[PDB]
Length: 250
Image (cartoon, rainbow, N blue to C red; front, side, top):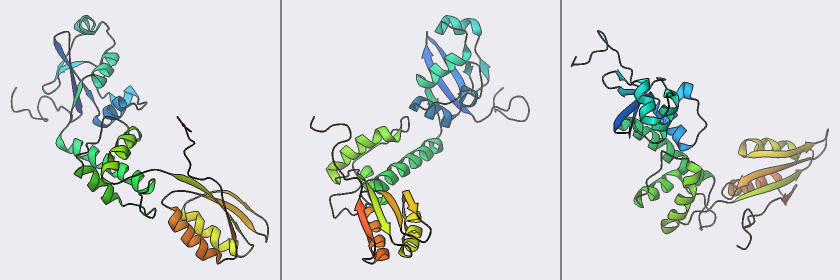
């Protein structure tokens, strides 16, 4: 009984176990910590993957399964799968420190990337560093929501960050017209530099390509572009950072 050895009676996988209290009785299900967290967060996940065990258990730690009768008398349905989803969204998932640390580092890294690659600061539009955004986030006692989407957290972080460092997001479209020859040097440069869209070139003629970049990459762009064009090509602006996305004056 005791001891628990995966080489005699039961193996007991290391799957994620979620528990939920309802009707007085406690239920548990074997699911994936990654699929469960992403599912509850609001990600269209499949039960065939998030649920390792398509059956409402009771004592997964020991290997005790529930009953269909009690399942319907406790939740009002026999669909063990449905009940599992409920516990996955309402119940609590049991994960080790590693499972929590891994998700934290990943989430933190993403936020720092989007803020460092898709955001600037009120200082000569100098792109901030991931280490800078991370430090400030921690210094301001900021706790990421691993049980939610990063996008939604962007507002909370970008707003709170204002206290330490004013961080804002801004996009912009670029348009460059290079000659026949000079166009061969610029194009190859813009390609890797950033997203290249609306590219039109003629046989032994000038090429007209537009470059899309945030309010941080614009620096490296204008730099390399100007140095690559050498007052030989033309550059027109497409979009401009202006408050006209959702609200104009309200």
